Structure formats: C-alpha cells, structure tokens
Amino acid sequence: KQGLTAGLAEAVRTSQPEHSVDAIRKAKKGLLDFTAASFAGREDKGIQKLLRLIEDEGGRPLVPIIGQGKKAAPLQSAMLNGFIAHALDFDDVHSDVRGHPSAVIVPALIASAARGHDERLLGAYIVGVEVMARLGESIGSRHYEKGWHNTGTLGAIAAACAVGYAEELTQEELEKAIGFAATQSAGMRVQFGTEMKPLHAGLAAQAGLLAVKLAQSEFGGSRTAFDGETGFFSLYGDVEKAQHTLLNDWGAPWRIVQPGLWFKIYPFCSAAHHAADAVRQLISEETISAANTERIEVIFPPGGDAALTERSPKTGEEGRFSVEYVIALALHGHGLTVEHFSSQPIPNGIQTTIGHIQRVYDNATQPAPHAVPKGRFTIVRAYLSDGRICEARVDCPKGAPGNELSEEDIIEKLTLTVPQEKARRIITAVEKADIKEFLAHIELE
Amino acid sequence: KQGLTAGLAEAVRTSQPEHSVDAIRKAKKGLLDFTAASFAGREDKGIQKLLRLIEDEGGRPLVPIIGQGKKAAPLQSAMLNGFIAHALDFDDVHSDVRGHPSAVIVPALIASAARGHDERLLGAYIVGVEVMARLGESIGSRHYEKGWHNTGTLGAIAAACAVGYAEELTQEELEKAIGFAATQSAGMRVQFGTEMKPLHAGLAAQAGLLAVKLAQSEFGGSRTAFDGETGFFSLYGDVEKAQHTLLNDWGAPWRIVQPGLWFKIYPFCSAAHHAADAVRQLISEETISAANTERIEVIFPPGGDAALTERSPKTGEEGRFSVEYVIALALHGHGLTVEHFSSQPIPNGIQTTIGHIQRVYDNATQPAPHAVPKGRFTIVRAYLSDGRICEARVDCPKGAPGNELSEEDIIEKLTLTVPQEKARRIITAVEKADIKEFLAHIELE
C-alpha cells in the first residue's frame, strides 16, 4: 500500500530518461531555448535590483548568473536565474504544467551541475518536466482558479525532484526532499502583471534546491507530505484526482516530448500566439495594414482568451496580455519583438487601432486535432475599405509541438543578443552534453 | 486606508507602540525569553546541519547567529535564528497566533537592527506581534485544521510588517512587502514531530525580511495582495472574518499585552504545562512518587489536550506532546528539563508508569475566570494504596499571562546556559534598550 509520496519518489529515483533518444533531443532543445530567453532579457532592470540584493548579502561565486557575467552562491543563483528566464515572458510553457517548467527546473539544475553530477543534468531535466507536468495534471483546476500560481506552487517540488535525480538521492532522502519542497510551496496569481510573477520561478527553484540540500544534510522531515487528509494534495488541490493521475504510465513517452514543451517565438502570452501568427499571415499574403483596415474581429472558442486579461493596455508590458495590442502593433508595421513589450507607453496611434479590434466567441467551430493547447484556435478577420474581408486561422502556433522550431529558428532566437560564434559554441556544448562548457559559455560578460 | 492591504499597511506604518509602557515592558521580557530559549538549544544538532549548509553557500558575516559564536548574512541569519529559537519547543506562544510569534519576528528584527534603526526594534517587535496575532485571529480555524502551520504561514507577513515598521517603509513599500511576504507564505503541519517544524519559523522570518528588501529595492509587486477573490484571505482562510477582525481596534490593547505572550517554564507543549504544574504540586505537598502511586487520572475539558497528540511516546521528543510522559517523568523524580525531552528513548520504567496514566474528560467543571488559555484547566489525580486519592488543579500555569515569570525566573532560564554575570549584563542591556549591546551579547562570541 504505497502512498503518493513514496510512489513519486520511487518513480523519480528509478527513472531512465537517457534511454529515450527523443526525450534527450528535446531536453537539449530546451536548454537552448532557456538560454535564448534568458539572454534576451539580459538588460531587464529587475535583474539589477536582484543582483544588488544578493551582492549585499554576499555569497561564494560558484554558479553563473546567466547572461550577467558573474557568479553567485547556488541558492542565490537559483533565484536569479529563474527570474531571468521568466522576466520577458519569452520562456517555455507546458500544457500539463499550466506554467513555465524550464524557468524553474533549469536554474535548479544549473546550480547542481556547477557542483557535481553534471552528467545527469539532461536526464534530470527530463524527470523534472515529468514531475511538473504531472503535478499540473494532478492538482486540479480549482488550484489555479482559487488564485495559486502553478509555476511557483508546483515548481519547488519539480525542482527538488530534478535535483534529487541528478544527485542520486536515496528513496528516504527523496521522500524528505519532496516534503521539504511542499512545505515551502507558494506563489499567488495576484502578482501577475508585476515582476514578482517571474520571481516566483526563481524562488521555486531555490526552494527545491534547498529541499535537496536539507535532505543531504540529514535534516529531519516528513516522508509522507503528499499523503493523507492534511497532505499536499488535500491542502492545495484534489487528492482523489492525484491518486488516479499522478503516477499512471510514468515515463516513455516523457511529458517533455508528449504533449511536449512549447518554445515561444514571441515575447508575450502564449494565448496570443495564434493571433500573432494569423495576423502576420494576413499582412504577408494580403498586405493589410493599420492604414487600410477599418477594424479587426478576433475569434476564439469560449474561454480561449482567458489568459489575455488586457483589452485596453497602456504599456507594452500590459500589452503582453492583450491580443488587441499584438495585432495592432503588427498592423502598424512593427516587429513582434522584445523592444515593443517594455514598460514604455503605447503610442496614441496604436491605441486608436486597439480601439478598432474586437473579440468574439465561436462555440461551433471544431478545433484541429493538433491544436496547442488542446481545443484552442484563433481566427483574425480584417475589414477593408469596400466591404472586403480577409481571414486567417491558427490552431498550432509556430514553436508549439506539431509546429516545431527549425534549426535556424533556434539559432535566430539565440543570436538576438550574442554573435553567431557564441550561439554556435553554446549549441555545440549542448549537442555534446558538455554541461561544463555550456555553463562556461552562458555566463557571458 | 481602503481595502485590507492598504488598511494593514497604514495601521503598521502609523503605529505608536512606544506610547504603551506595558507593551514596551512586555517586549523587553520577550527579548529575554527568546534569548533564553535560543541559548538553551545551542547544542541542538539541527543547528550544525544548517550552519554547514549556509557555510557552503557563503555570505557576509553581518548578523549574529544566536548562541553560536559566529555571524552570517541577513537572510541566512533569519533562517538560522528562527530555527534556533523554536528547536526545543521552549520559546513563546500566543493564543491569537495559535503559534510561535517571537521565533519568527525577533530573528527578522535582529537582522534589521544589526544594520541600523535598532532604536525601533522594541516598537517593531510590538507591531510584529500585533500583526501575527491579528492574522491568527482573522485567518479562521479551518486554516490550521486543513493542515497549515500558522507559525509558518502567518510569520512571513508578520515579520515583513515588523521590519517594515523598523525601517520606516512608506505606505506603498509596505503594501508591496505585505504582498511579497504573502506570495511566499507556506508551511505544513505534516512536518510536526520533525525539525522541519521549527525550521518553518526561520523560513518565515527569512521570507519576511526578503519581502522588505525587495520593496526597498523598488521591485515591482501587487499592492493589493490581501484584497479580492484571489487575495490572501480568500486563498488561505476566511475573507469575511478578516474583513471584520483584521484591523478593528488596532493597537488598543496591544496583543503582546492582551492576551499577551506566554513564556514557558517547561521545554514542551504549552498544553501540558497545567498538568506539569499540578503534578509538581502533588509531588511537593503529598510526597507521591512512581513507587507509591498505582495510577493517575488526568482530567481535561473536552478538547483541552488536542495538542498533546502522543499518548504513548517512545522518545523524549515525542514526550514533548505527551501529558503521560510529563507526569511519569516527574513521578520518577526527574526535573522537567531540556535534557529529558531529547531524541533519546524513554526508559522502560517510565514507559511502565506511562501505561498507568489515563486521560478523562469533564464537560461540567467550570474553568476559572483567569484560566489560560480560555476555558482550559487540568486536574491531576493520583491513586495511592488503601484506596486513597489526592488531586491538584491548575488553571493558569506559571509563565502564562496573569501568572507571569518573576525577574528571578527570567534570569534562571537565561543561566541554563551562561553564567549569572553574563545573564545580568544581557538583562541590563535590554532594560536600558541598548540594542547594540544586546546584539553583541547574544552571539556568545
């Protein structure tokens, strides 16, 4: 009669992710996307606030701060590197997680790898994603609806499990590490729209790393924190659901492959990517523009735009969650790029165009079987001068599983910030599973 | 201020605790009890596990680790000193908090006072207790019953508010710090019976200190984390209750005075202190002993022993939550002292005596008007040869508000560990509000 805590600890401990060629390939691509997203945010001012904070605390310079040209202590690095990866909303997402797995897991593993077992990082990454996906599937819808932020609340446990795999924790050590992570698990969706939201990823990475370090120190703790009427799932979610779903069909195929990580080509809310692809198609094929369009209708399935909470953004940052701003920015001839999603105010011409973009809801159109997320689509319809219309539909955006990034796409995202030579050195280190060389290259200056 | 977050921030910011002579006296006594509890646990092996961890991380030696003879970084010191204060269950309790306020608040304030504003520490301590008491009152009974550990889940916000008062944060900065603390709030009762339970106090102190440092760094965050249907009280407790109770009659009377901190004379669960007082009375006045007692009946009102979850402890640590062990230990002629509540096994003779002690429940006996906690009493009845019985009743144990420690009790608790001359110098520094000298003394080199 094995409880959920022991069940998860055993599944993690005895995993053999390196036996899956596809999962290893996907983990290498994940390291490259994580690096690209972190580099693209290297000038974000929140990073400097956090660097001044940890410099005031002090710490041994052991782990690189990605893209920042310095090192810091392991737990400090986990906080910093999680924030950096998530700061621009340019990092990866996972449909099971309903959140951002690599921004939590990879910082924890970077801190572990800088200090041993780096030969297990890729496998640990696969296992970490496996846990976070399954936690997201198991916790229940009410968890997010009530106000918890999955990236934070499930990230600490997933990071503890990834690092626990990497460091070859015993069954008892891993059970305790899971409980040490669960008893720190936190993060509130009220922080959305502020830089505390990406900081949740760093604090979750830090909490999971601390959980492993406590277990390795022989610190005492519960071995059954998932179990019972006061266990983690009863407290934060749906324990019946977790009992049915958490461990079923563990591993191959790994969740990092199926349903798979989605690597973003746009630095804004994944829920706007369909519209972004569609309007770009219309601008390319039909030469539409803000000047020649009277107005726009954006068609979602009911609830498809729930994450796009900004209908009248004033800032590029607020515009990250506005399908109106995404479409209007493209119609005005601008790239859907990092520089246009900052705290600077949206110019008045684009705001005028935003006022001519409306959302409508279509409960009859059947989503495509390969849609990401499942059941999602978006149609963009432009109204031109003489009553003419044109439309484009996207169900699986570029970068999502089923519409994967090309070789060249990965290189392009990496070279947003660094020369071609740097990006190629990074790619080669990752291809060779040379984690020491990877870590050396991603520090930058 | 309008809304709960702004309201609490304003209540904290504009507090004038220094106008309350009684509150200042109580805060000084709380500092001395915190110090004595921390000193008494200085040999705890968990402390060395945590010291090795933070030494591996590194940090500037800025803040004393109480009783350990070294300094560490502010956030590290908060973690260490909260653990140290709570490690033996010898630290203070508060009925509104349903938890251990000083083990959270004083570590955060020590880290803040070591870097300035030390003249505000005593006031900040009062304000911190005010917040944690009100959170414990406002969150609702279901919070603890569901499985959350109030010391952990309410401590970060209380510590952020104490340090925010000490460092004179603005209204906006305090609103943000409250949210930075709330979005980290965590801690599960499944960790009871392990040293992770006292570590919750340090992790809460650390999270509250981080919240203040983020607000001071101009880090972005929600200013309304208590408010709305995804706010802290809706997520973790009873938002209706909090709307009625959180801010009402603030600071009048200060909760550190009424109902007041309880300073323990025994290093075990407060709920056993009545029985401890009673059995000692019986041993003193009637010369009962393990040898001449057939059996014991211990009488509680319904629910009075709910916290005493161990009826058949195997170790002194488990014995901390066993009225049977407390009574049996006293009957066998041993002091109710730190050395008898360690992880070492309970000897077979004491276990035999434990088997002769039964709990019974009396719903008719009226608690005394001065009972602490409200409605609580304990009667100890000893059955001797020839059918004789003797009984002793305790309603307000020594150390509880209304039956406060003498000066001599305070010095005795301090000298469990250090010579009388050292303790007198510590007390003198606290009496004069010489916080710098106090901080110098409690490092123990």
Image (spheres, coloured by chain):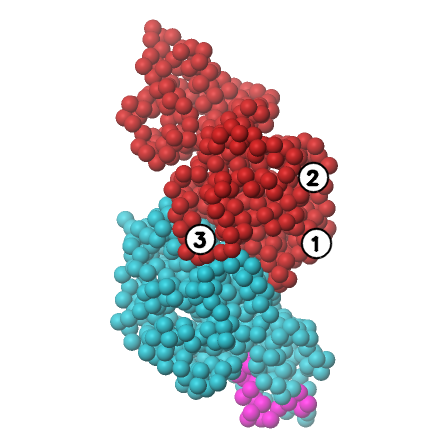
Chain colours: A cyan, B red
Q: Secondary structure at mark 3?
A: helix
Position of residue A250 measured from the top left corner of the image (x, y, whole percent): 31, 64
Does A364 lie within the magenta span? no
Is disc 3 on the same chain as disc 1?
A: yes
Type of the residue with mark 1: Gln
Q: In the figure, residue B131 lies in which quadrant?
A: top right
* Residue wearing tag 1: B171
Q: Mark 3: few, some, or many residues within 10 Å (few <14, many ≥20)?
A: many
Q: Which residues are magenta?
A: A275-293
Q: Earlier in the sequence, mark 2 or mark 3?
A: 2
* Residue wearing tag 2: B17
Image point (41%, 58%), residue name: A209
Image point (53%, 57%), residue name: A57
* Residue wearing tag 3: B54
Type of the residue with mark 2: Pro
Residue A302 visible in this rendered orientation of the protein:
no
Q: Earlier in the sequence, mark 1 or mark 3?
A: 3
Q: Is residue A358 left or right of residue B78?
A: right
Position of residue A58 measured from the top left corner of the image (x, y, whole percent): 51, 59
Camera-side residue of B429 and B294: B429
| Disc 1 versus disc 2: nearer the observer | 2
Camera-side residue of A257 and A308: A257
Position of residue B362 measured from the top left corner of the image (x, y, whole percent): 47, 21
Residue B437 visible in this rendered orientation of the protein:
yes
- Check the residue under mark 2 and report the chain it is in: B
| Disc 1 versus disc 3: nearer the observer | 3
Disc number for residue A17: none
Query: Magenta stretch: dominant SS?
Result: helix
The relative height of residue B278 versus residue A444 in the rendered view (above or below) is above
Does A285 lie within the magenta span? yes
Type of the residue with mark 3: Ile
Camera-side residue of A28 and A154: A28
